[PDB]
Image (tube, rainbow over all chains, first blue to last red; front, side, top):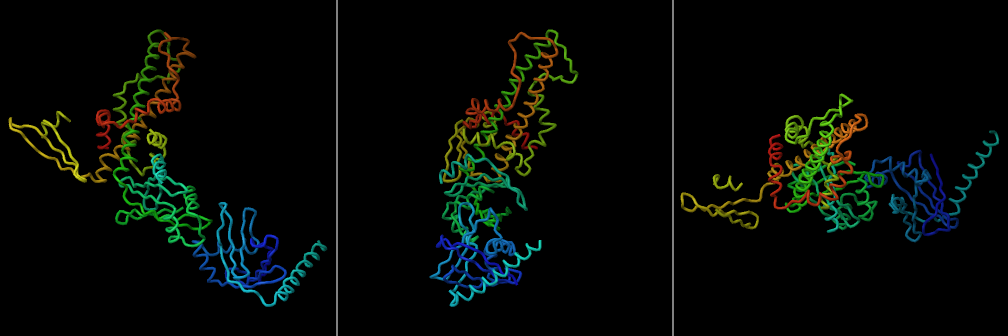
Length: 144
Length: 211
Length: 141
């Protein structure tokens, strides 16, 4: 079971850091649950393996290569030449995310979202986890 | 558009490797559309397309991750997997390429090119270049006779050769045209797959198109 | 018809119906006149291929080979004249001195000055005079 959270900025909110959380079982291709927030409110959505198959086979692409791309985009595997961009409307609960080359954008995928009724609870969970994570590296560095 | 045509006219010939055969193509691309001409060295085909057809056809062939036709045009400028079919005479070139880091596909529905433009693009140009080449041969020949005059000037008074391997027989066209006919005309005039033409003659091609 | 044409290759008239070219001969035979009409449909692009283009490509590339070998002959005669002056310890009348041959300049000057007339299509008259021999030869090959 893998979790991966990512600090993001929606284009609609340049000054607000949004946070993209990803949870999945070793494999983003199999399907995942996604959660977005901005410190006052949070949203969640879901995508399946067949959705990714359909996306990748409308990418004209081998699935897996598009999965590596997704690893770059959503799990922060992007490189210095990589410029992804994220767009979401809180009113419509519709997300999509794109790729910037040739001075142009390329929508990579797009998700149906929903606002969570308990933002604060997912928030506590995420940040407890993060605290734990911090602390571990701290102890390790000490020993080293 | 007509700019596409006129630029194409000045476009030299490329050479294409299909898995089935080879091809020669001259193409003129703009952000406005494209001007192509393709031939298999027995038949020629033509296709001319603007950004609207580009857009709709890409959508059909390639759907989502959508873009400006000019972006595709730019990638085509980059210039992948090529295939074609001579459906009735629509030589539909089928090209799989890598665009946006991903597989791309387009069909050039190249109908038989028109005899007017066929003149305009091969024959009139070919005839022009062949004649210009003959003028080049004549001028190099007169230069070699100037050189023969200069060498015979040495030969009339002293001027013995030191390097016993620099001898040149006096230049006379007919015999060398004959030896060209016999020894090397077969290998030369071999049509092949259109490669030597795209290799060496494109300079003169563009020049003759300009003139 | 042959006896009439071979000299010329009597009066002739030509007309193009929509696609076909129609060729008319006004002449005489046995003192009597002879009238015939040619009915030539637009030729096929296999025919066009084989009779004009592929042979004409062939022309172009063969004369390219001509130019290449004749350029290298120019360079070898340059080597001979150099052997004459630099080590042969001899001079000439100075009225026949020729520039050492380089194909790049030669080409730039040919295409700047001679090319406007070197590639001229014209009536097809110069084509059918100057190269029909090579035409024949490459058709055979």
